[PDB]
Image: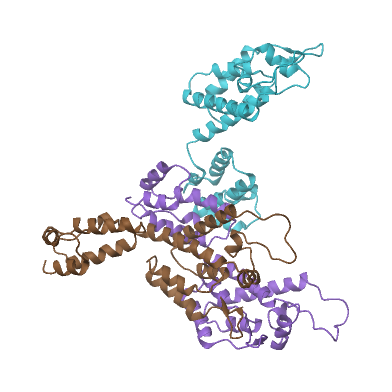
Chain colours: A purple, B brown, C cyan
């Protein structure tokens, strides 16, 4: 990564083995779970493209997903090149070259080049551009690797509501829809797939009800 | 977080992986237990809003609680905006803008902006404002996720008083009432739900008695 | 009603018995069904408040609904009076008085007064104001008197899709939601509650599919 030194300049320092291993261990343990994305984001703080390929290349397993991601990274890169055309005429001696999708992916650029772009004034955030592609591609994966739809979430005849509400906001946690739609899902689908005994109870709370009151309301059921 | 450097200035430094993992592990092990709040408080020393969303977003599990907290954070934020109106006329070139609820929640502000507010003179404690909302919302959770009322705490017919007194100040530990009320609960409810054999014993100690003397008094019972 | 005469003026003429009876017969046959509202609207063309109370008062049966409507008409009328305050000072000799909620409901006004307001220049559409209250109150009734939710609409294991799609846009016909939400319901819920054999078929059509192609696609199933 590129970090600030004591002297007050930005210099490159290598990433740590127990950081590396922590990246490995996350993937081992939580596979495609959503917590992987904030986790990634923290461990990618101040990271280079080069370090980001290192992290992706050091994965073992889940090769269908790893290929889907690659292909997303190239699509997003192809899109970078499309949206940002190359600039007019020859490159100035006094200046350094604009990046392409493949420089952002780290492929066509060298480390010193990656440090030039980020440390220079203005700086360009080629990490953050790759980061969105990674996060976007992470959404693709998460959405695919979900095994059950939100409509299929229902309360058992003997299942406590509580255990059901947990299941609901876990699956709701894997839905990516607008907040307004997710509000609509909350007031609607939760009660609808609730069991008759609690359903009866919840109808008596009326509208305007909040989760602690619903959760304490269906406790004996 | 924003920490003081050797040179004698306040600069941002990233939070550590075994700090991150220690946050994870606390949540894994002690879930909604009260010790989570001092623990949080220590690990949030010198932390940014941005780091606080990172910590909240990196949770797995307990999604009903995570949603209740979110909704508390937005309520407390809505309340920030209500109580503190925007200021008169355009923003000065010489000055930086006042925060809103969403800047405190980290959402509408950038890191450099979060460092401007905290490092500037006077400094504004946007961490400590979010921290209270987190702690307040932590109380909401703790109180909900308690499974048993203080009136339901009683001593068995064969249960040592000692094991009962431990249960009492654990449940008393999850009551948040004024100290005077909690004093009233101490002298009253403890003896009242104590078993007849020890109850008899405790009546002989009279009033003015302290816990070592009660605890040694009902030892053979 | 108030109709235009051959001479080229607006004069009142009475409503016809087989019009009256047609109103009766609609209510007899289709009770609370949605077709009642366009039907009403056509038969209320050029109608007075007085004629509208006549139509409501001549109902037999469905007295719970008739009371709910009354109470909606008074609420909407109370709201008219609230929103439109009485005007400044005494009424001019040269002018006629502004209506209240009860004049719109026909109650405090006389026919000649109802003809003054409508025929005068500018004219005021007191029919159309009552008409919205009637239609609004008709929505309230329709929504209540629906017996089954859209989530409860599902395809049988032996039921032709066709018979199911008919049921869907009938129930969708009793949903009053924004078009965008109703589009969301169309692409989503229809396929989801479709039977496994057809569901399989529909998955092969891919996205972008239209109703004639879905309807011909699941025909042998």
In percent of width and height, residue A2 lies at 64, 84
Give the residue furthest to the front. Answer: B208
In percent of the image, x 42 and y 60: which residue is there?
B139
Q: Is residue B175 above or below residue A135?
A: above
Q: Quadrant of the N terminus of chain B?
A: bottom right
**Which is more toward the observer, B89 or A28?**
B89
In percent of width and height, residue A164 lies at 41, 56
In percent of width and height, residue C111 lies at 66, 12
Q: Quadrant of the C terminus of chain B?
A: bottom left
Q: Please tell me how many numbered marks the rendered image carries.
A: 0
**Which is more toward the observer, B105 or C53?**
B105
Q: Is residue C181 above or below residue A73?
A: above
The answer to whether residue A23 of the structure is visible from this angle is: yes
**Which is more toward the observer, A177 or C200?**
A177
Give the residue furthest to the right. Answer: A89
Q: Is residue A83 above or below residue C50?
A: below
**Which is more toward the observer, A191 or B175?**
B175
A52 sits left or right of A192 in the view: right
A186 sits left or right of C84 in the view: left
> Quadrant location of residue A178?
bottom right
In percent of the image, x 71 and y 88: which residue is there?
A112
B141 sits left or right of A126 in the view: left
The answer to whether residue C221 of the structure is visible from this angle is: no
Q: Is residue C198 above or below residue C86?
A: below
In percent of width and height, residue A108 lies at 72, 84
């Amino acid at each position: 990564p590129i970090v600030q030194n004591l002297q007050g300049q930005m210099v490159h320092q290598a990433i740590s083995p127990r950081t590396l291993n922590a990246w490995v261990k996350v993937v081992e343990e939580k596979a495609f779970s959503p917590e992987v994305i904030p986790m990634f984001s923290a461990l990618s703080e101040g990271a280079t493209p080069q370090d980001l390929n290192t992290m992706l290349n050091t994965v073992g397993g889940h090769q269908a997903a790893m290929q889907m991601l690659k292909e997303t990274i190239n699509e997003e890169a192809a899109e970078w090149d499309r949206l940002h055309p190359v600039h007019a005429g020859p490159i100035a001696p006094g200046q350094m070259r604009e990046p392409r999708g493949s420089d952002i992916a780290g492929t066509t650029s060298t480390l010193q080049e990656q440090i030039g772009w980020m440390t220079h004034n203005p700086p360009i955030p080629v990490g953050e551009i790759y980061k969105r592609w990674i996060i976007l591609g992470l959404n693709k994966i998460v959405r695919m690797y979900s095994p059950t739809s939100i409509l299929d979430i229902r309360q058992g005849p003997k299942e406590p509501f509580r255990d059901y509400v947990d299941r609901f906001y876990k699956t709701l946690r894997a839905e990516q829809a607008s907040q307004e739609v997710k509000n609509w899902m909350t007031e609607t689908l939760l009660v609808q797939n609730a069991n008759p005994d609690c359903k009866t109870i919840l109808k008596a709370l009326g509208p305007g009800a909040t989760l602690e009151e619903m959760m304490t309301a269906c406790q004996g059921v």
